[PDB]
Image (cartoon, rainbow, N blue to C red; front, top):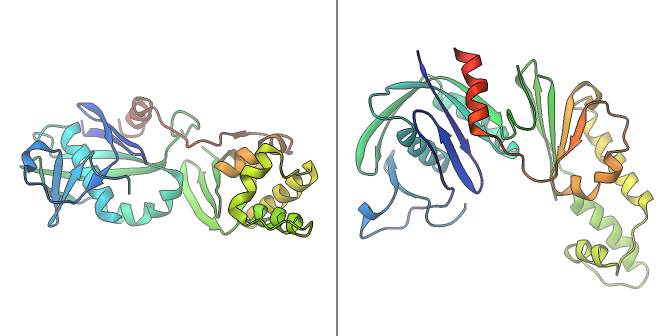
Length: 276
């Protein structure tokens, strides 16, 4: 039995499940420590990274957190594993580079001062939300509607067929509202607008939100037919448009504006079905 490990490289915390399970802060630093032995740390490819301290932030950062997680998840008798790697949806545009880095490769590194090594046999890279907000066994579309960018992740026949980015976001909607307001004699900038709508200093008609939603959907159309997928709208712009999104002619969909999360144990059970 090839051992399996799940690692979720989240923006706030990292979680892992192998022989052992754990969670640690996604903070990292490379700052020099005069008492290195008092810290969680990895040394890989000449870089010493302190784990769980420093700041929330890179290729070398993911590698540091991943290698640390794998050293914690399994003892040194484990020489190779199949890996399920869960990433925030925006970072899914790194999948191709990560597979080439990891699949079939051995890694030598120092873990809290101890030489360790781990080989990645097979590998699955999937967006956070796996096994908790969407299921694959398999036509899923995650639309992250951000301030400046739409990130699209399409999982078809249970594998990623597309990641795409579009330069359209709430920033553009607030730029349209700003224009209208200043034409009334105001002198706002874009960053003022959101808070002024919230507290009523700027009134916005439901028609304006509907038009902006239609611009988003038309920008997405060249890339993906949302009717054909189980579609999850996420991101802060999905919050702004929730009530209008829920009125759209889409069969299987959902609005979850906050970052998607995965039950790492649920992700492990799904992974055992893939490889065992």
